[PDB]
Length: 304
Image (cartoon, rainbow, N blue to C red; front, side, top):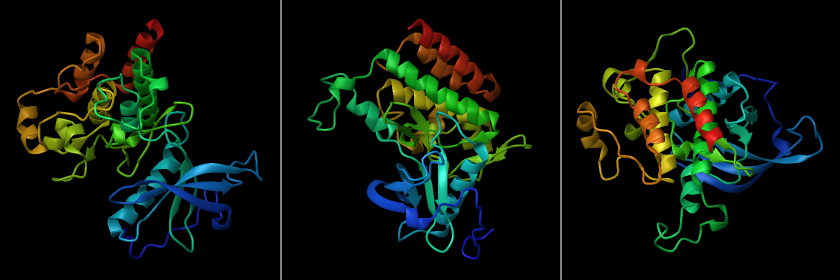
């Protein structure tokens, strides 16, 4: 393509008028972009006069070409996958005659890691944290429920023949009503009509969440997302813990080849830990599918 010479084409069904978008407080600032809260007047067809709170993803002043390319790619991926209860859904975009604004559903309780960490059982909270929410402490049931919703989001994603490639607690958002939503589709790819996605030699996927076929064989499939989902489960059941604690990524490469796997999280059942271990099977085709994970997780959640 070439973003420095590409004119974003009009797409009237998604286009939103700039004069009806009012930018508010920042929600996030990463290395490659920015997200702010906004009021979008009329974005909901049902209430054409009503302003709805939304989140807006946009470039920063020091953006690279790749940053712009990533933002366009995320927007296009979200058009293609369609709507699901457990995915941050695309609402609109301001693409003409000005900065690219990608408008999506607002998740008022923020990213999953901090959501879990603020909702930890007392004492493990040492030291003094002003951001805790003891009135909403996580039960085992809440954690399973969290995993089930995310599994449903990925089941839907896989059914659209989309790979996310960057699954992780930092890329999950939580709504006012505690709905888990997969976000950040900047690295997502459409693998319709190809057997697998071909990774570059040195990719842009965080190593501690990467399946080995991708790390060592440069292949990415839905089963690679399953590996990542297993790491995400581990993050969930440690209530926002960071993976392979104490192991730098440079040492992880060889440990993985040798069959190293993370230990069971403190307050998790063997049944759930085995499910994690199943996701980290060396043979991709021997990991469960997202459909099987949904079925298993649903059964577990029902019993609880």
